[PDB]
Image (spheres, each protein chain N blue to C red):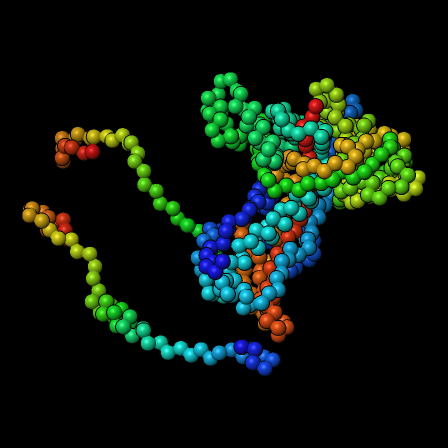
Length: 50
Length: 414
Length: 51
């Protein structure tokens, strides 16, 4: 079923008639994650390649 | 007593779990303007075999094909309406956005109260004595064990209980011996895990309470009822007459009471074999649907949900070891007239739920408010010229029960 | 007001006088649009990199 985020922000001195609105939100996160890295050391065309 | 804050003080709130757990998948957008006032779903088929040692037997007594139905309908309006004076309302409440908050909660609370009443009225299975509360782990494990024993596989099974009983289970969990995570969680937050005893246990404070209803005398059946599949293939309900009751009392049997047939046992539906509860076989039970009084001579005509089919021409649909007939002994669970709040356990595919959208009324301003996925339509008008404003909130539900044999009530047992 | 067994409302005219300066600001922005520019450094290939 359709469950929508409730804010009760608008309808403040406004008439509502459209029953076909559902509020969906994108959520952004930032994390510190420990990843392993590989160092290719091909002598030809530059050596250090991380 | 002159300065007043605008912010309304916080109030009390119930909780919404039953509508979330029940099935909202199959019946959704199916009650349209073309379908009508009801909609029906199909039922599965069952077959039985023969045992003969010969092969050129192309002519014999074959099976039969009978089709069943499960009908779902609409309910009554859930309406809240207020009449007021717009000046006294708008002294401190513009746009009437303050009245909105305690209205949608009332609507959804009434909706779930009705849903709980419907579920406990249409459930068939019963467990434990109503008197004893839930105290130990077996009290919640038995529901999942019985559900697995009957044979339900496709779906998910849930159980709902009151706040105090959960507390007791968490207290018992605090006494564990080796699981530090569980012990620490129960010690600190006093919350039980999700999978408790093989069934998902839930805590809810909003749950219907019911009264037993006075009864007395060793009841027994009078006339042999009709429980054939050709009769009960559309409703899974049957009407039975009881004799030997008390002389004349009003309200002999309330709605939701469980009537237990002593000598008729349950059957494992697929293998068609009796059920053993470790120490004693499990007997059949049914639920009263409508209030029944008793007339002189102790005759009670009662309609029960859940049917003990023992068809003799279509054996493949049997669900009870032996046919109930006249002179049998029956009982009613619980004591005379106590009031209790039952605990529920049910499969996902037991009772459905839906809502019917409502068109906007002509020449009257209106709006739509969404709350837990339920759309409430509000209409405002000013009939009467005495500063008599009128606002009304409307919502229309629809209910359906698929199989009564996949749920019921359960208590603790001594 | 109640006004002799009716509900006649007050007249509420609207004379918008605050939008002219906002429109002027918006037009001034749209006349001179700006974007992001990358500047080079004191290196040999910084110009090509920025380009």
